[PDB]
Length: 7
Length: 99
Length: 274
Image (cartoon, rainbow over all chains, first blue to last red; front, side, top):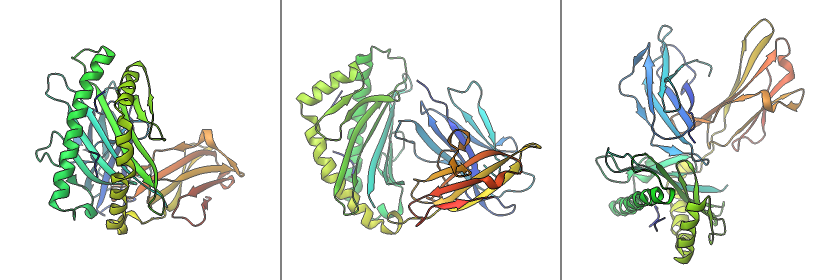
């Protein structure tokens, strides 16, 4: 299952 | 930094003339990921070569497998041509049946 | 033994030639099972292993949603990195991301990963405690401060210890015949004179899975590190792996050299001697 924040 | 590809050209199975096999060109340890890889039969680019999905190792360096079905013969010479920004000219690596 | 699930993503910007290309792949141990390519026609997460094809239409819908969202996030992140590093909008840059988890033989959570690299070098990573970040440079420290304040780690912690683990255990069961196998290496040696006074010995390991393996040459029982040529372990294409190690030896002295092969599929390490 793939994972469900910017720099 | 940029990293130059480590290139390996080999068959899936030890080669036997007349026996169907797969010709592989594995490039690894490179960066950036932009790269062009061709398999050559007697100097001529082989059509319809497939390759793996772009992935990378723990150190972030990329690896790809290029491959095509083929049947080795005594006469036919095979090689892999790798075109990458770290190479002043494409590296052409000949298939050696024991490498 | 233990197992891992990893997703690897690569975003590459291409000024002028449109938006960044995003490619993601998923693995369980050394077996790939999904892919997504932003340049492809489907715009879908796609199966790349037989044991995942059985997943229903909802799986493929959800995975596609999740990976497309990542794709947009890293597109934004590339632009921010340009700013942080004061780089021209003309250059091509790379943002890589890796995440996933390890479990023990009993399926228990062992460790989680969530890390980024910019232009091929560490940018920021979640530490093992899953509560803190390691930033590689001043640019990443900006991100670290933001993610600490926004408690970004707590979420990742969750997925890593929950969804990630469940998925791996599920895949390990569904792909049991493929994933819980070990294929021992088939070994042999080759030998080629290179001159009147030297010859090559090459020690081969073929058809093995998983990819982890150790090949070592000894002479009269002493490891020969620095003179061995060792190639990177490579895929055969059929789901198994290959490796060789070679040494150049004085002609007539071949018998002094032994190749030692270690792999989890071998009850006892093998020793080969010409």
